[PDB]
Length: 290
Ligand SMILES: CC(C)(O)CCn1cc2cc(NC(=O)c3cccc(C(F)(F)F)n3)c(C(C)(C)O)cc2n1
Image: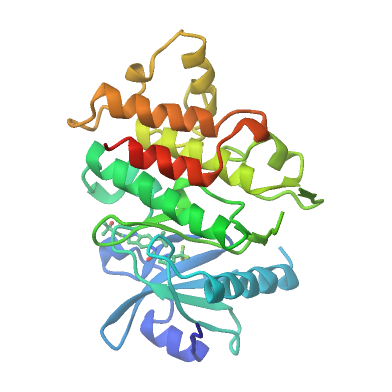
């Protein structure tokens, strides 16, 4: 692929000079995605996300350059799609196809009055996100920030993995001094600085628990604070998955929720070598809707 090279002034124009009012009150600010703020825009009838990046300049410049490198190689119906970018001006900007149902985080939480996702829709989002991670692993990439904030949802609730700024090209276990990820999602070995696709798998399991419960992975004002902990509550038969299923669903049945929870639990083994590879996660999520 290649991408349109936008003037900073063009992207200022399409985002109403990066207007900071929310979309919900007719503004252009949609939310935050990594080390940047992201604005809604129109280029010739095409609705776009413009992500303007604000950590060192050379670090920020590296993640921008990484995102372009990953989006050049990787094109799949379960990955967000870059249209262009802007280096010339002050701020570095990435221009994507708009995702009209925003992030899985926001929908799981029914942000801005959106209705709760059904069990049927959740199953498709899961299969979809796993098809996304699979393409990235097949094309020898490690995301390193799989979380519901980074699974976007299009007009038909198609799951789209996004934010490849930290993605590592990994032919196949390195280790690192700069440890990166969102704690609440990261595996043991990722938090000790190991880099391996097997960490992406753990992180996915957290996202399956988010899907099953509608609980965000961390919540300071909740017990337990870490959704992960609920695995241990369940394995120690203090509670069943039934006690934790999102109550904002009328269409979840025991069999398919347990099926999904079994994947989440397999995904979440503490021993990275006992976890299934994304290919097996696909097989199991596809097997789960018979
Ligand atoms: C009315 C309604 C149902 O509330 C929906 C409103 N809504 C719509 C959104 C679209 C979004 N994102 C994208 O379009 C998008 C597309 C590609 C890439 C990227 C990223 F790389 F910048 F992360 N973001 C967001 C993000 C995820 C950027 O915050 C939030 C939203 N909220």
